Image (cartoon, rainbow, N blue to C red):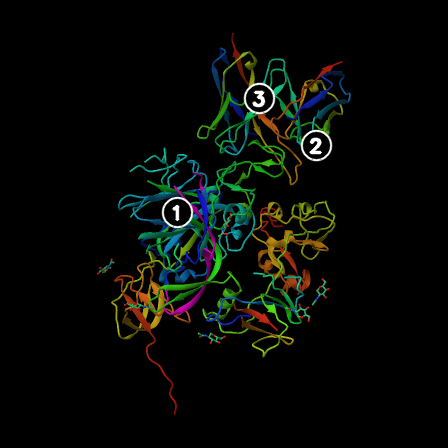
Amino acid sequence: VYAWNRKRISNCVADYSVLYNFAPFFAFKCYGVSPTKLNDLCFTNVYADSFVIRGNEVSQIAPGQTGNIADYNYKLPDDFTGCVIAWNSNKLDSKVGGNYNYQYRLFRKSNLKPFERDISTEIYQAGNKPCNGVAGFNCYFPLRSYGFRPTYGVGHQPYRVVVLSFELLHAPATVCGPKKSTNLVKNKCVNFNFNGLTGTGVLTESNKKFLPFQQFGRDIADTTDAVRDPQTLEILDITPCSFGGVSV
Amino acid sequence: TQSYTNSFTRGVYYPDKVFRSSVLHSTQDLFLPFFSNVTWFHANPVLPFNDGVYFASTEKSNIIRGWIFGTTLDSKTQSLLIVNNATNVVIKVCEFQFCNDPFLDVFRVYSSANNCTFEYVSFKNLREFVFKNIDGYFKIYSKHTPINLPQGFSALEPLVDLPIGINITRFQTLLAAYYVGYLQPRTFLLKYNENGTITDAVDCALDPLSETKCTLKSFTVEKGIYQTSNFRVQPTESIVRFPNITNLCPFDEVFNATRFASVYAWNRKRISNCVADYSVLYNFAPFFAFKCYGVSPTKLNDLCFTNVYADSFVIRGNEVSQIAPGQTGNIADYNYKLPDDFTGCVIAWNSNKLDSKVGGN
Amino acid sequence: AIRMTQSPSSLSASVGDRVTITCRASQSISSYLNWYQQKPGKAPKVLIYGASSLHSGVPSRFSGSGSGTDFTLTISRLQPEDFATYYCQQSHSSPRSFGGGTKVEIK
Amino acid sequence: EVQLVQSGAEVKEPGSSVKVSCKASGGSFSTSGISWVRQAPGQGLEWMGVIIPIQGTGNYAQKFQGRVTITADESTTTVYMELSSLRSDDTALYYCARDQHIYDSSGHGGLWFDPWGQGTLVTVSS
Amino acid sequence: ITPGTNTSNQVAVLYQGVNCTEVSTGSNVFQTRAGCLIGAEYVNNSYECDIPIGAGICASYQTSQSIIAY
Ligand SMILES: *[C@@H]1O[C@H](CO)[C@@H](O)[C@H](O)[C@H]1NC(C)=O
Ligand SMILES: *[C@@H]1O[C@H](CO)[C@@H](O)[C@H](O)[C@H]1NC(C)=O
Ligand SMILES: *[C@@H]1O[C@H](CO)[C@@H](O)[C@H](O)[C@H]1NC(C)=O
Ligand SMILES: *[C@@H]1O[C@H](CO)[C@@H](O)[C@H](O)[C@H]1NC(C)=O
Ligand SMILES: *[C@@H]1O[C@H](CO)[C@@H](O)[C@H](O)[C@H]1NC(C)=O
Ligand SMILES: *[C@@H]1O[C@H](CO)[C@@H](O)[C@H](O)[C@H]1NC(C)=O
């Protein structure tokens, strides 16, 4: 957990409905998004951060949490949008004599910033007496090994955790769900869906001066008034179709 | 050679990649404050980084070429090297061993280059760059404008975004006179004209007039008296006062009993005159989480209670849901009832290995 | 830079007697003192750690106490197999300085 | 508990170096300090240095710095101590021991060396 | 207190309901029943009210022009 692995996912179509076939977990824990809607969205990037904790600490893998893990080992941002997947791995990560291949950081001078990894093995100095790298009074070793055994209770058994963080920026989308894209229809009232941005309106050719890095435009009420087509990089103006009041 | 200069209004960049036209938009971000104090260098330690760097160079022949970012710059950690050939920009994050006085000859910078986890390849002129390392991206904004620091305005369009998450604290310039400023978390009011270009900006914390301009959400302010803000005196230090108590609370004997009581004759223990560390309760029982009502489990160590009561018993699984305020059932009616205004924590763990016998317990 | 001084260096007692050995530190080491028992031709074994705790398997006759700069190891009833050399070690800070060592002999 | 087994005896000359192995049976490796304690013939014990295998380096007392090198082989679960520039005062029994360092919450309880090797007699022949 | 930005960027500040001791800050402090007025030169003359400050004190922008309170 103190040296949690991180993998970057980009330039691919992500089908989140096969994640049930890879790990024997019971449900997602998705913050800011719903697990069933993941296949209908495009994200600029995905990050899969994997590690092992024990049962008690699975509750700490969540935005706004505090503890040993959330402070010194693995911290999630308060504005987190993603999904946490944790499953019991007592059959794999537990030995009869004890599994001491998994460790956690117990002491640290200050709390971790979100998504910060600290792999320093320096001796922690609780007091003022210098340690000079040697354990002693008020000189602790910050890393402590979990002792995982098959006879431990469900709260003390190992749990494998994978955190998926969805970077949804203004950049062009790179990770999308399986979704076939139809032909572009202009000058007609249609239900459009650009990279998961859904709406209803009339799409017209535009002469707005989008800079090469921009991808969409907003309005006074933060309503998307222009878009960039993901395939043919042109600028489309979105207009409400047609409506009015009718008096008798 | 280190001189000092006023930055005037230089250093405004597009904070987002959303197109806006003919609008005044308020954004809080790392900006270089107006009329700041920039350091002017002439052609050597390493400058700090802080929250961001604004680099400016009035040049004509591209003498300055590259930059170095990192924390120790001694191959003990990953460092960012950004150089450029006649056309190709070379960006590397190897664990370089930089020389004391890096320079370029018309390469004598890093004697070693190991563990490269990322590689990216792509009148005077005033070139302005803003480097900031927020989130997990190293954002570089650039703007080259012909001059003859001018008392004018020009926005800096974004140029490069790199997913490198290298911790950066120090940086240095590489060449084969330049201005440096540091970004601070300021609130700005930006003006997008008809073509979507930032043409003016107001720094809301510069002076009372700019506070008025930002409060009105406008650049022109009419004659009158405007209620702008509220002045407050901020605290100087923190004071903590807790009672004189040294004994530790006896949570050992509650969770580690040989046999728990029956639910109808539930055991109760009183806890007082002690310091209770609720972070060791995880080491006594193999439960999965607390169920705290009126309080949060992580905050328990920051509170003082007049008394604590630990009521212990054994039920079966179906009835664990009944140990909660407002519940009804056999247990909540005839055995163990909790008040509707309950403030506490319920801890339940399976004990099938202890409380179950082959013939029945 | 912390030194440990023992007293006496060699005491001769009989079986069933009470043996008291003192271990003094130049400066306070809290409760980071240990007592080791070494028999000739063999590696030392732990008897007291933390100045007040008994290791698993240690007979109840051994007892240690004290804190700060004054410490004492006490054997309530001496035994024929309790004649050995006793070393006191401080775990306060580097270096872990062993005492001069007290040798318990038969009267 | 954990069992420690060392290598055999060594006979050397002043100005040479000696490498002594200490193989742990196992159970807390890469987090347990493998301390080395030497004992001169007829003299008291002396602490040379300690190594935590995950640190990679080795810490030593302010009497052996500069001529003692301790390294750990994680794959073989063996700790190696290399004492260079041997002299007359380097003839002793060389034990390897494992630290525990149980601390409750304030400083009560300290380190102790429960497992010791059988001892590696190193003789610096003249 | 400000004349229009078309006229001058010089402004005066009124800290409402505080004594002129609990107070960017010029050496032109003045004590009105409405608060502490910084940046306005009090004048013994009286004119028509231009910018009402309160409790009978008004401010204007008049001549080398500056903000005066009266
Ligand atoms: C995208 O794909 C369409 C057809 O699949 C193709 O006509 C178009 O050129 C492609 N554009 C890009 C930028 O890949
Ligand atoms: C910038 O700070 C220096 C001292 O660090 C000071 O001498 C200089 O006057 C400042 N710049 C301005 C424009 O006042
Ligand atoms: C926008 O660009 C056009 C292009 O000629 C120019 O005429 C116009 O003045 C620009 N807008 C502004 C506000 O300058
Ligand atoms: C500027 O605004 C003031 C309002 O206080 C007005 O009296 C004056 O005539 C204006 N001047 C110009 C040139 O618009
Ligand atoms: C301000 O305080 C001083 C003493 O500190 C007092 O003499 C004076 O009357 C006060 N004035 C007002 C307006 O509060
Ligand atoms: C106003 O007059 C009083 C006395 O009549 C005098 O003390 C004071 O200084 C005058 N104020 C100014 C600004 O001249």
- Give me the C-alpha separation between circle 3 and circle 2: 30 Å
> Which marked residue is nearer to the observer: mark 3 or mark 1?
1
Quadrant position of residue B327: bottom right
Q: Position of residue D121 (x, y in %)?
A: 54, 15
Q: Is residue A30 visible?
A: no
Three-letter residue code for mark 2:
Ser
| Outermost bottom residue | A248
CB of mark 2 near ligand 2 (< 8 Å):
no
Ligand 3 sits in quadrant: bottom left
Q: Nearer the viewer, residue B86 or D119?
A: B86
Structural distance between the alpha carbons of marks 3 and 1: 52 Å
Task: Say if B298 sits above or below B192 in the image.
Answer: above
Give the labeled residue for mark 3. D63
Chain of the residue under the numbered disc 1 shown in the image? B
The quadrant of the image that shows the N terminus of chain B is: top left
Crowd rating for badge 1 (residues with CA inside 10 Å; few <14, some 14–19, many 20+): many
Q: Residues within 10 Å of mark 2 (few under 14, many from 20)?
A: many
**What is the quadrant of residue D104 in the picture?**
top right
Give the residues in magenta: B19-46
Tell me the residue that label 2 is attached to: C52
Residue picked out by circle 1? B178
Label 3 with label 2: CB-CB less than 8 Å:
no
Asked whether the residues under the numbered discs 3 and 1 touch, taking CB atoms below 8 Å apart as contact, a structural biologist would say no
How far across and how far down the image is residue D21, in percent?
49, 22
